[PDB]
Amino acid sequence: DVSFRLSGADPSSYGMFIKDLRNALPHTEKVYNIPLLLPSVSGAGRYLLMHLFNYDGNTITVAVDVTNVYIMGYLALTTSYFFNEPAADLASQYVFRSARRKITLPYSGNYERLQIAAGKPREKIPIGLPALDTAISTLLHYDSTAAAGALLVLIQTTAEAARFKYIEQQIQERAYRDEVPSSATISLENSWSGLSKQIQLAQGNNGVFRTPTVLVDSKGNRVQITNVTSNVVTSNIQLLLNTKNI
Ligand SMILES: *[C@@H]1O[C@H](CO)[C@@H](O[C@@H]2O[C@H](CO)[C@@H](O)[C@H](O)[C@H]2NC(C)=O)[C@H](O)[C@H]1NC(C)=O
Ligand SMILES: OC[C@H]1O[C@@H](O[C@H]2[C@H](O)[C@@H](O)[C@H](O)O[C@@H]2CO)[C@H](O)[C@@H](O)[C@H]1O
Image (cartoon, rainbow, N blue to C red; front, side, top):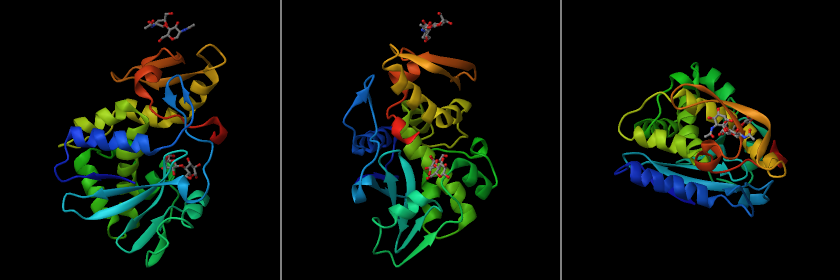
């Protein structure tokens, strides 16, 4: 398991949590030096447990699919909650079996469905460490509209931060003040899968991408990623989604 506490949290301990979150994910190959996530893992070992503690010391445990860094659901006191999706339903046969009930949320984990449930796109949802504190607190007592938005915070401050160093850095800047994510942040989130694919495909194409990727950059500019010498590949991405899951 990995575990982050918001009390005493500062950019340092957050970064160290995000470091642990990346290191808990297993892999047997790096591709251009980037850990490559497994095509699949079997039974309970597919699932990473994150213990998260809000500023007051209350806690949820979040189950993460180690092959893709998707949140399956979480344990809040004695009630387990899981997205309405086959993967999460699978996950529920291995994690938090001893919860007193299990609730299935009325949406999948997809950013699109979570946005409808929340009634606002990610662009307009502040994120940061204080926002991650709100979100932990929310998920402690069921409320599905509120949870949509608490989960969109949670995905971005954990999973999306572990995937990209840039988004980890965006969170660390917001240690004490929330802020809507930059467009570049939405851009990377949306591109994770195509980047993972084109990183893997570059490797017998002399590090050239078969299909270029369009991103927005940190300065709000549209930019095009064409091979593995780009900063996105060299510095930014930290985990690759296996093409055997794309
Ligand atoms: C791989 O992508 C790099 C960009 O990171 C390409 O080099 C860039 O492309 C043109 C010049 O050819 C310029 O717009 C950029 O300023 C270049 N940037 C840097 C930092 O060199 C490179 O051409 C691509 N590789 C191939 C074979 O096309
Ligand atoms: O979309 C971002 C969101 O991905 C979810 O994955 C969705 C997937 O994109 C969609 O095809 C399907 O309906 O549900 C998937 C979940 O199994 C993740 O669940 C979530 O954590 C974010 O990564």
